[PDB]
Image 1 (cartoon, rainbow, N blue to C red):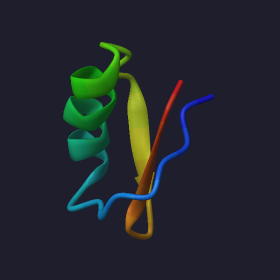
Image 2 (cartoon, rainbow, N blue to C red):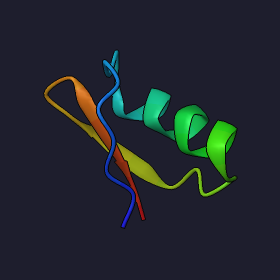
Image 3 (cartoon, rainbow, N blue to C red):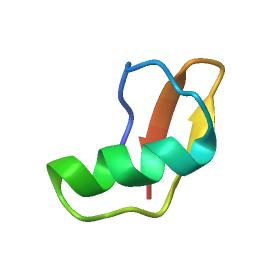
Image 4 (cartoon, rainbow, N blue to C red):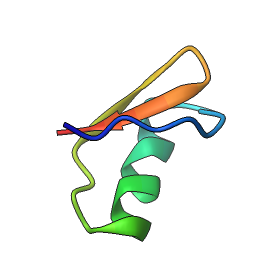
Length: 37
């Protein structure tokens, strides 16, 4: 679904990230990248 490359500080950031772009705040960080569903 959502896959991005911006530095995760935590999965919970990916939420605000995915939300900033779209709103689809349901996500998880990988390593230092991040993904929404």
